[PDB]
Length: 231
Length: 232
Ligand code: HEM
Ligand code: HEM
Ligand SMILES: *[C@@H]1O[C@H](CO)[C@@H](O[C@@H]2O[C@H](CO)[C@@H](O)[C@H](O)[C@H]2NC(C)=O)[C@H](O)[C@H]1NC(C)=O
Ligand SMILES: *[C@@H]1O[C@H](CO)[C@@H](O[C@@H]2O[C@H](CO)[C@@H](O)[C@H](O)[C@H]2NC(C)=O)[C@H](O)[C@H]1NC(C)=O
Ligand SMILES: *[C@@H]1O[C@H](CO)[C@@H](O)[C@H](O)[C@H]1NC(C)=O
Ligand SMILES: *[C@@H]1O[C@H](CO)[C@@H](O)[C@H](O)[C@H]1NC(C)=O
Ligand SMILES: *[C@@H]1O[C@H](CO)[C@@H](O)[C@H](O)[C@H]1NC(C)=O
Ligand SMILES: *[C@@H]1O[C@H](CO)[C@@H](O)[C@H](O)[C@H]1NC(C)=O
Ligand SMILES: [Cl-]
Ligand SMILES: [Cl-]
Ligand SMILES: [Cl-]
Ligand SMILES: [Cl-]
Ligand SMILES: [Cl-]
Ligand SMILES: [Cl-]
Ligand SMILES: [Cl-]
Ligand SMILES: [Cl-]
Ligand SMILES: [Cl-]
Ligand SMILES: [Cl-]
Ligand SMILES: [Cl-]
Ligand SMILES: [Mg+2]
Ligand SMILES: [Mg+2]
Image 1: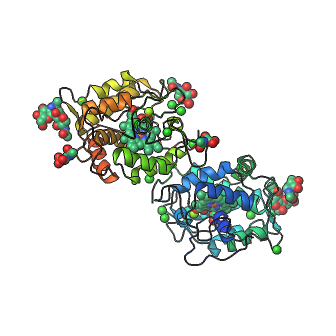
Image 2: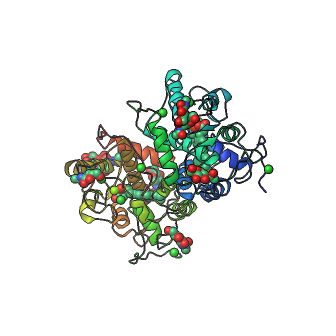
Image 3: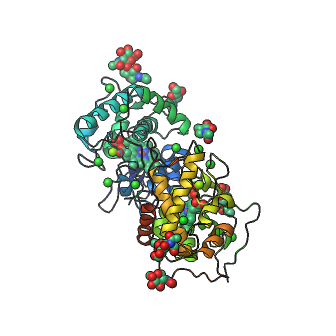
């Protein structure tokens, strides 16, 4: 019913492996266009068993990246400073290169994490957050690192652990996480199953909280958290 | 003819916005103030006032943050302090000091009495009102929030009352039209008000808000980061 197909050149994609994977399976429109908030809620439920609370807020902020009244394209979501942030797991900082497309060299840090284990977990996820921020601080003179970016980065790490793995423990098989990022594909052939446990603020926040404590974080002085309001 | 004024009944929801409240009171928006989508705001702003989508779409997307629903808000949701609703309102009390939702004559007194001895409000009077209303909040509200975000919104709101009740090009409005708009949330059609024949856009509003800004004698509160409260 929902086969994987690589996006063609008319097919718009985002910096989000979550939404890109849903589009690549037709849970969202395969062209990544004309997406409403209710379409996000239904796709997150259908693909991942993610519940509306977190999706509705993310989607309302996503709408700010679009000139349209009540839809965005996946490509709109690249707008730097709305949701898109520096120290991404698999994308370059906007200031240093391409903030939109999967990049293997950036992904290397997450790929190689939890060395010697068959899983990623909260400990490895925190170490990756720390290493990816340190890389941005070392190479990007324009890095934006406030409470807003940090909260989002901990919830994004909670999402990859939760959707590709176990939503209760935040432990995920490495091969599922690698396919999710590298191919934006549900690893069904490799044994991945949609969570039987609803994924909610109440499951994600405890995981994001533990990842937070394992990240050793401090905000940049002199930066006010902000949501860029227009493209 | 198709859009008569009716006072809201006791279960009709209203906002801190005379703009949206007036549209609801004429049925350009649902008279009950419920189930408002972004397209409904765009159509109502066009139909009532000849206001174009650019500014309405952004305001409505931020308004959605005040609602727990996927793609609608009520007019009453928009009272959420720190999303759009701000201190030093023209016609409402600060959230910290009282009622941030309902029209209040004692607050409105400053705008009512502005440009003394003239029959119009204009950019100069609008700036003096912004200065006096912020001075009042700084004096009486220990919790006043006064950043570039609240100031920009306050200048655009004053550009809106001048533009919709008056001349969208000059930002001059008849005092009578402005007083009816705030006090009754009614289009003063009986008293001679006509919908702009000139589209009201970011390009007409921003120059007026800019000149109101320069006439406001404004400075930000220094320790405060601009923020949009993301949930109720
Ligand atoms: C449905 C479940 C979701 C999952 C599992 C998910 C997962 C993720 C993950 C793991 C990242 C990190 C990518 C990286 O750092 O390289 C990410 C980033 C992002 N997501 Fe999502 N996401 C979801 C929903 C959403 C929604 C609803 C929106 C917006 C409407 C959104 C917008 C973004 C954006 C703009 C980024 C880029 C942040 C950055 O710069 O890395 N996501 N998402
Ligand atoms: C359509 C034309 C509009 C006009 C002419 C207009 C006009 C105004 C005016 C003059 C005020 C100031 C009230 C005061 O300070 O006492 C105001 C406040 C407000 N407006 Fe609007 N508005 C419009 C559209 C909107 C839209 C689309 C939204 C939200 C979706 C909105 C939300 C608000 C809010 C929340 C306030 C309260 C701010 C405060 O004083 O604390 N307005 N509006
Ligand atoms: C994440 O996985 C790693 C690797 O399995 C865990 O760290 C190891 O924990 C074992 C089991 O107690 C220790 O004996 C090893 O010495 C640890 N190795 C390293 C390099 O850390 C880690 O505990 C896991 N984290 C969570 C929250 O489950
Ligand atoms: C707004 O209206 C006021 C009052 O009419 C204007 O200020 C007056 O301007 C006249 C003629 O230019 C001066 O001679 C008066 O002394 C001013 N009166 C007061 C009360 O100050 C003001 O210029 C108008 N502003 C704009 C931008 O049109
Ligand atoms: C997820 O982890 C919990 C807690 O260890 C476990 O009981 C549950 O069976 C796991 N879920 C699946 C489907 O494996
Ligand atoms: C209007 O809004 C509420 C949510 O606040 C919804 O549950 C209700 O069904 C809607 N009613 C109509 C008539 O659309
Ligand atoms: C100011 O805000 C704080 C935090 O919300 C609140 O507890 C306090 O009562 C407020 N103080 C005044 C005088 O409004
Ligand atoms: C608005 O002001 C302009 C510039 O003075 C004027 O030419 C125009 O006619 C005014 N509009 C109306 C309907 O009076
Ligand atoms: Cl961008
Ligand atoms: Cl930048
Ligand atoms: Cl590691
Ligand atoms: Cl970190
Ligand atoms: Cl299969
Ligand atoms: Cl902005
Ligand atoms: Cl109605
Ligand atoms: Cl409130
Ligand atoms: Cl307050
Ligand atoms: Cl005055
Ligand atoms: Cl908030
Ligand atoms: Mg990024
Ligand atoms: Mg107010």
